[PDB]
Amino acid sequence: GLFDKLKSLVSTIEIIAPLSGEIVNIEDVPDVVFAEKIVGDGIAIKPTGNKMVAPVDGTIGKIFETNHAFSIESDSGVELFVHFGIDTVELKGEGFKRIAEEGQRVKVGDTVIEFDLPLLEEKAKSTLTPVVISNMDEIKELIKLSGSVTVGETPVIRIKK
Amino acid sequence: KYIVALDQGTTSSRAVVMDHDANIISVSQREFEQIYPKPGWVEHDPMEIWATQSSTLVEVLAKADISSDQIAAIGITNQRETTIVWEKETGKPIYNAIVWQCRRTAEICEHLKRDGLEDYIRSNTGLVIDPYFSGTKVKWILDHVEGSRERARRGELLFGTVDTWLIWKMTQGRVHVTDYTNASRTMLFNIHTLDWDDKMLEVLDIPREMLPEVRRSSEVYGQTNIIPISGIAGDQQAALFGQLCVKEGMAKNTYGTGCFMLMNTGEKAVKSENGLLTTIACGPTGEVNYALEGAVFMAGASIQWLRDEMKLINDAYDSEYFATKVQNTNGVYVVPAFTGLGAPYWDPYARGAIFGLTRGVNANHIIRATLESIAYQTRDVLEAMQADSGIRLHALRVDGGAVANNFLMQFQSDILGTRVERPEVREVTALGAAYLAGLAVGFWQNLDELQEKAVIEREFRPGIETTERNYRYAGWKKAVKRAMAWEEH
Amino acid sequence: KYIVALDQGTTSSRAVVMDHDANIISVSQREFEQIYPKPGWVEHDPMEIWATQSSTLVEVLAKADISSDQIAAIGITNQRETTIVWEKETGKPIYNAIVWQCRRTAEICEHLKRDGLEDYIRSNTGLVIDPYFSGTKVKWILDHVEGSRERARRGELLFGTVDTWLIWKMTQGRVHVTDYTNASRTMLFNIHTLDWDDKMLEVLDIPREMLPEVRRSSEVYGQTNIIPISGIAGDQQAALFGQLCVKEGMAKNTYGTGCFMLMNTGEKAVKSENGLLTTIACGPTGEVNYALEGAVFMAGASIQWLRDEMKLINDAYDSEYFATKVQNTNGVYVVPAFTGLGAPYWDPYARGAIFGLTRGVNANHIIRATLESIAYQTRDVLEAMQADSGIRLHALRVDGGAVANNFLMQFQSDILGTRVERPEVREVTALGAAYLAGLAVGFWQNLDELQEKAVIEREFRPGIETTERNYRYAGWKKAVKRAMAWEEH
Amino acid sequence: KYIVALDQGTTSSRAVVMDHDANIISVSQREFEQIYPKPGWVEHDPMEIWATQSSTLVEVLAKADISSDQIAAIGITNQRETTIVWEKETGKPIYNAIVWQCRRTAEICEHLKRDGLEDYIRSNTGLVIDPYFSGTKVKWILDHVEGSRERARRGELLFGTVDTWLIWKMTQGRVHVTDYTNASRTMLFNIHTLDWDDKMLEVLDIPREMLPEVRRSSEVYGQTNIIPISGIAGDQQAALFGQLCVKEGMAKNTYGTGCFMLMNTGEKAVKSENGLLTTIACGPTGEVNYALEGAVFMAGASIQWLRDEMKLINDAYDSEYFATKVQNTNGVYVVPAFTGLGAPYWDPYARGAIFGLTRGVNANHIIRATLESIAYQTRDVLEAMQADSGIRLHALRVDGGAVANNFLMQFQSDILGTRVERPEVREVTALGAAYLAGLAVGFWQNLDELQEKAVIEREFRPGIETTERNYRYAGWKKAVKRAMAWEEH
Ligand SMILES: Nc1ncnc2c1ncn2[C@@H]1O[C@H](COP(=O)(O)OP(=O)(O)O)[C@@H](O)[C@H]1O
Ligand SMILES: Nc1ncnc2c1ncn2[C@@H]1O[C@H](COP(=O)(O)OP(=O)(O)O)[C@@H](O)[C@H]1O
Ligand SMILES: Nc1ncnc2c1ncn2[C@@H]1O[C@H](COP(=O)(O)OP(=O)(O)O)[C@@H](O)[C@H]1O
Ligand SMILES: O=C[C@@H](O)COP(=O)(O)O
Ligand SMILES: O=C[C@@H](O)COP(=O)(O)O
Ligand SMILES: O=C[C@@H](O)COP(=O)(O)O
Ligand SMILES: [Zn+2]
Ligand SMILES: [Zn+2]
Ligand SMILES: [Zn+2]
Ligand SMILES: [Zn+2]
């Protein structure tokens, strides 16, 4: 049933898709902190299924108690914030499931949180999944890719530090 | 050469001495008793403010080594609303001071509403029917003393607010003046007409005889012997000023005994449609300006509560440390309506409540919850402020004593999803009076002489938890709605 | 010669050794961890009750100097509802014990109501749809473990309550029995038919395979090596018994971790129409009797709360002293729904709240308020008890640990307007098991041998403040109604 | 695959599980009662260490998810000196354990001195006449039980230290062995001859019959069912080891319940001329090595004292925060001789004292003073260490639980005028046993496999206050000299 066991095809800073679907303008997030990049900048992603993963080899910072989001520090001094959907914290951890732990180092691709794309599909307010860089101050240039992406595979952003 | 400001606050009395270059030179604080003679009631003792305020002066002057010879003027700042009556001859109170919080004259307000004055009072006072302001505290006094009204028509009876009382006790009985800021607070004065309301006065059965003289917030009121007193402004307003409020759409939030959020509305009396107060502030020369205000009764007080009655902390400073030992309030909410709800609730009936407790909740959840209440309230007031004025703040300038709380500061920021600018000198309410004093005395000439002592010391910006804010606030919202209407009538 | 009782409670585990003359000879208490893995959740660790209960035995035996040779039997008393599952082979739990308070299986109950079983469950269990009882805690367990249901049909999985678990761990795996008292609590057993409900079992997806053997509350269950175990009864019931409940209309109130008020209804299963439980107790020979029960989750716990998390007191004993330094709660109310509301509210949603706070309220108001909650709740339960059974108590016999609180005792009395009889030996829940043990062993023959160790030590009678009771209770009533429905679903 | 260590300490019992790569995988702590049946006395309950130690194992294994199948071996670490006697047949103690601190057998020591054995005992035990060690606690026991000595010649009576007791209770009665480290502590064993002293044994009236088997600190003692137990070493020594003591002149200081400072003296039994202990440690293969040791009874305990009896703090962690709110102890000194003075004082008569108090001193002076005592004592021991061994440390490697105290750490540094290296894994005492276990099992082969998990996490270096150290220490010196000889005889 799961190829999780089998071997995969294996191919300045590049940030990788930490979850999958269609990329989106931060600007369209139904939440201001996001949409005005108050929290920082990056993109978003309408999601396709199953799981959230490290997008940089770094170290997972904090993991939300209701496990719907997490942050992480790249070995390259970048800060990432991944927030699944919006107002998700009201589902109180239902659909979510904690693969990793609030302290480890990870490579790109390592499973971080698993999820239930459909329970979440009608329960949640929105499903948008912002991916932003929070420490926008220590970053020169930041670029936004487009279209479709695939987990731990397609990159969404490129940035010059 | 230097000005000297006087800050007589809910909690305590202070005395600041600044130089021309506007540097805080020496300070004196002295806290004073709080009496609750009955539940929803608060009262302070006129002679104690008095003793405490006086005493504070000397000690500052002394501390720095300075005399009558080197002080340009006296600037005066006080706590609002808090009503006082006193036999003219004597220099003695016919009662205790009723504090701004004290919910006593609550039924009275209930008549006022019963009659139909909500509308009126709104429109001319810019105030709102509530025990919060001077008016009713006056009548309640006159009403609970045999020889009062009459004794006062004959006029042996004096009314006043802290500035007025503070002044007269210095101009040895000579001067009876309140400022423009002070007066708006009273519920007796007319903000457009800029003079005592005949209606209020009547309706309330107050006698023009006791009312003092109402004058500019920068003027030489008189001389006193430590010398002239050139400044007067209600505390919240003197801080608006020290922040250099002064221009349209400009705003600050003061975190002290209570929380006061104000925005300068230049020369336009914006009519609040969102639980807010239309009141007076100053424009750059100490002239009359209008403004929107959000009052929140309990802020720093709560900390004092944990500190002094509950006994969970030795210092309010410690709250940061414990509140941070916890990550979450663990479900708990603290609605600190210890003395009703103010803006924009205005429910003199609600009382303090605690919620969401379970066996695993401990002291630290609780403290932090108290700290949180602060930002919640703040935020309540703010949203109002915005709707009303159609403007969207991008930063919050702040100041106050509680503002030294990195935690609270930050949390305040996250919960708003807005930056928070914390000024390098926290003691702004003081500064304000000074300027009003100095300016009025040629001590300074121009505000511009000073768009420099106003360094920002710190910026708090929204952390990642800012995403969580809506949920957390809804918490708050439900909690609040449950503390309401607790008392009865 | 002597019996030895075992009391394994919510808070702690104990071991009492009595003589034939029924005198408390030596005791051993040992408190144990309380885990709250999440808010409305409570859990204890099977191995810890275990370790703690065992350890307590030895130490009592040792303390007095006594051996296998002089002990007639073992009487067993436990905390109710608290569900446990364990791999038969091993002697190891597949989970932690879910405690009677733990509100986890709350949604489940919500289905049950959604389906239509309220009526059924009432009528056959005498219980009421609520996370309080065993049933749902079982399913919730089976539901959150891969190899469970199936592993349990094959039957390598054991269910049980503390008595059952306590037994099996002593009869080295031999015995799997619960008593009649215990079983009623589960929500799976039928009180008329006096056997497991096929419906419940189904509906809940429980497998007859795990259920133990259900037997008389006085019988020799087996032998163990410290020897036979002749007694078993749910704690509340073993205290009904030690008070010599035993006859129709007879009642007691136990003040411990919670509060349990029960009345013997001889052989008639009175149907509660007032938020009460119809459940089983004993008649004079340990035979099945019916009874009305009022459960109140939080009593002594609150004190522990102030004592252990809030940190206001070092000892619960101290509460008398501080609560008495105050005369009034000063308006304050404490609704201790830390783990929902029980009878007669039964709202697994309400949470702890505090009310009527103002700046003058301090620690001592608060403590006392907590103490007060006790009598209020008690009183709530009582009125129910009366309505239901048509009888009007004239006294309240009581017992429990909190019952050493003159203040509370008295206050309890005033607030009821009824006398309160406090028994000279507080450790009654124990005594109960013993008798059931002794009796069953010819250790005693007749209850009558003992209508003598039941001396009354004190009578509390209604003081003049008893006139004030209605007001004060209305306080309570309003407070309660506000803590309700706090959590969400 | 993994080793599992057992650390059974004065304060509590622990269980660490490491991997081959030597990473701390899961831990379990469980604190246990401390009984003071009388002043200068301390005692623990054999069944409680037991219960606590056992229980801790399971819970670690469980926590990580692991079985009998994946664990290479069991490493064992215990608290020293603490004497135990127990009926062989039963598995039951004839008494309570006498702890290393307990000053009971103090008169006995007084005879020993009266007789002339100071010299002897020094020279063969390397120990010093003091209630601190096993010997006298044994005799005191045998002396306060009717059927003892005789019952023990017949040999139904077992002696042992925690490792020995811990072992036997696991090798179901099979194994009776102590390690080399353990034994030196007893005052009955001969460090040169490396075997029980006939003299001690006599003089003390001890019977070779109870003494266990004495074996290498790395050897397979036997197998147990959770499997073999390959490691054993007295705690202080297992930490010497985990720090990779191992070579001449190498040293560490452990900050826990007490303070223990040790230096490896390879294969030479250095004779202390400065209040120090000559005792055994290990060389790289777990072989016997000698060493100099400085024992200090009270360190972390004091904190617990403030924390648990005095009640000034909720957590020991908090001590940093309060102690830092003060800058100075304000003159105060705390000599924590709660259970006599150890090295290099060795005065079982001194008792705790506090000094230099004046009206302005408060809680925070006090706490900090307690923290300070730590470094003072440390420093006392150190100077001894140096004189004795002629070597001058340049750094202090440390470890222990208290070592997380930046304040203390630093202060320790200043007061010494020496750098302090704090290791990245504090839980070293554990690690030690493991290696001894692993190694002995081919789990590792070479120590060298590991001169890598020993990262330094932090360096504390002497701040400017280091200049002040002499004065401050003289403070200390005077204080100490005043707490001495408090009790009488
Ligand atoms: N670290 C802190 N955190 C919270 N509150 C603080 C802290 N430091 C001081 N305070 C609070 O700040 C208040 C002092 O505010 P301030 O503006 O000086 O006094 P006032 O109420 O007279 O206007 C008090 O209510 C006090 O309890
Ligand atoms: N003076 C007292 N006042 C209030 N509560 C008391 C007092 N003494 C003991 N307690 C309380 O009594 C309880 C012990 O009740 P008991 O019947 O022994 O225990 P259990 O909850 O296991 O049934 C605790 O909840 C404790 O917090
Ligand atoms: N921040 C801290 N400051 C002071 N003492 C601490 C701190 N954290 C823990 N402790 C102390 O450390 C000790 C634990 O030391 P450890 O090496 O674990 O235990 P043991 O005494 O069994 O060897 C306790 O005595 C405790 O009171
Ligand atoms: O409305 C009263 C205000 O003046 C409050 O000021 P304060 O917090 O300094 O007492
Ligand atoms: O329903 C649970 C009862 O057994 C409570 O008994 P307890 O207070 O002794 O834990
Ligand atoms: O001499 C006794 C030592 O083993 C002390 O060790 P401990 O601090 O871990 O209890
Ligand atoms: Zn969220
Ligand atoms: Zn102020
Ligand atoms: Zn009980
Ligand atoms: Zn240790």
Image (cartoon, coloured by chain):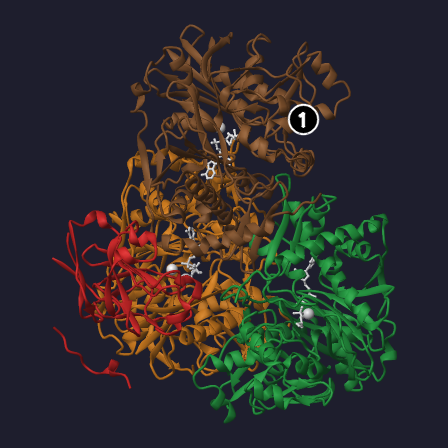
Chain colours: A red, B brown, C green, D orange
Q: Residue at 29% across / 50% down in the picture?
A: A36
Across and down, in percent, residue D189 comes to 41, 67
Front residue of B94/A44: it is: A44
Label 1 SS: helix
Across and down, in percent, residue C237 comes to 74, 76
Ligand 5, seen in the image, is in the quarter at: bottom right
Across and down, in percent, residue B192 comes to 50, 24
Above or below for C433 versus B80: below
Q: Amino acid at mark 1?
A: Val
Specify whether tag 1 is near ligand 4 (CB below 8 Å): no
Asked which quadrant contains residue C211, the reply is: bottom right
Across and down, in percent, residue B255 comes to 46, 36
Q: Label 1 crowding class (10 Å Cα cut-off): few <14, some 14-19, many 20+?
A: few
Q: Residue at 85% across / 80% down in the picture?
A: C447
Q: From the viewer's perspective, is D37 left or right of D27?
A: right
Q: From the viewer's perspective, is B38 left or right of B170?
A: right
Front residue of C393/C52: it is: C393
Above or below for C217 versus D79: below
Quadrant containing the N terminus of chain C is bottom right
Asked which quadrant contains residue C304, the reply is: bottom right
Q: From the viewer's perspective, is A70 left or right of C112?
A: left
Chain ID at mark 1: B
Q: Residue furthest left?
A: A12
Front residue of C312/D158: it is: C312
Q: Residue at 59% across / 30% down in the picture?
A: B133
The residue that mark 1 highlights is: B203
Q: Residue furthest bottom?
A: C154
Above or below for C231 versus C429: below
Q: Is residue D187 visible?
A: no
Asked which quadrant contains residue D59, the reply is: bottom left
Front residue of A24/D193: it is: A24
Q: Is residue A148 visible?
A: yes
